[PDB]
Structure formats: C-alpha cells, structure tokens
Length: 50
Length: 50
Image (cartoon, rainbow over all chains, first blue to last red; front, top):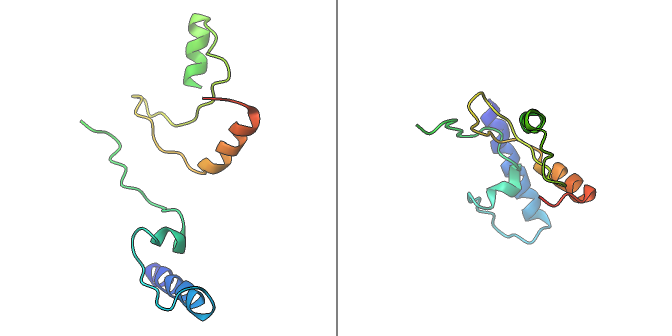
C-alpha cells in the first residue's frame, strides 16, 4: 500500500509538470528522482566495516 | 559530549570556534545525523569556522 502512495505522488507531480510546466514528457530517472520525493528516509548503513 | 569530557579530563580547552555534531555507539564509528541544512545555517550564523 505505502508503495502505492509514492507511485501516485510521482505521477501527479509528472502531471503538474505536463499541464503547464516546461515538460512535454516526463521520464523519471534516479538522478532527478530527488526532486520528486525529496530526501531518502531509509539508508544502507552497514554500521561497521570489519 | 564525548569531546567535552575529554577536554575536562586533561584540562586542555578545545580549539576555539569549532562546532561539531554526530552520534557515537560505544566504539567511535560515527553515524549519520539528519536535518543538516538547518544546523549548517546556524553554524554560519554563529561564525564557527570548522
């Protein structure tokens, strides 16, 4: 379910970037993804090395 | 807090105008902290250089 919310949010921001923005066709990518949901929540910590 | 105690243990003042932040987990491997932009503007406001 919670994934569903992030998916729809990515979509609706694509929609506002279609309706009047400067984008004719959005295509989400990992580098620009930061703009669409902001800072990551979880991390890949690996709290220690050895 | 750690560096505080250590300064006190030897009586040496910490080098002046040094701000820091982080987390420590009983072996010294520092861990990420969040919200960094706000702490950054505050440190710039206080004149701390490091």
